[PDB]
Image (cartoon, grey):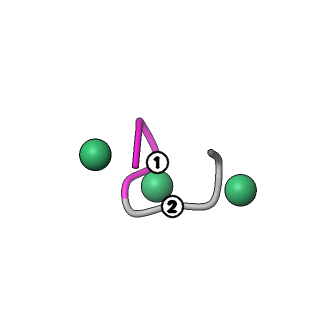
């Protein structure tokens, strides 16, 4: 990250 920080959704 994003809205799943820390990822892997990115
Ligand atoms: Cu992330
Ligand atoms: Na960031
Ligand atoms: Na990813």
Q: Secondary structure at mark 1?
A: loop
Residue occupying the point 65% across, 48% down: 9
How far apart are labels 2 and 1 at the CA level? 5 Å
Callout 2: few (<14), some (14-19), or many (20+) C-alpha neighbours within 10 Å?
few
Most common SS among magenta residues: loop
The answer to whether mark 2 is within 8 Å of ligand 1 is yes
Circle 1 crowding by C-alpha within 10 Å: few under 14, some 14–19, many from 20: few
Marks counted in the figure total 2
Q: Quadrant holding ligand 3?
A: bottom right
Q: Secondary structure at mark 2?
A: loop
Q: Is residue 3 magenta?
A: yes
Q: Residue furthest top?
A: 3
- For label 2, the residue is 7
Q: Are marks 2 and 1 in contact (CB under 8 Å)?
A: yes
Which is nearer the eye, 4 or 1?
1
Question: Which residue shows up at 41% across the image and 38% down it?
Answer: 2
Residue 6: image location, x then y, percent: 39, 63
> Which residues, given as a range, are shown in magenta?
1-5
Task: State the residue position of label 1.
Answer: 4
Q: Residue 3 is drawn in which quadrant?
A: top left
Q: Ligand 1 within 8 A of label 1's CB? A: yes
Identity of the residue drawn at 51% across and 61% down: 7
Image quadrant where one finds the C terminus: top right
Image position of 5 with respect to 2: above or below:
below
Q: Nearer the viewer, residue 3 or 1?
A: 1
* Residue drawn at point x = 46 percent, y = 48 percent: 4
- In this picture, is 7 found above or below 2? below
């Amino acid at each position: 990250c994003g809205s799943c920080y820390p990822c892997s959704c990115m």
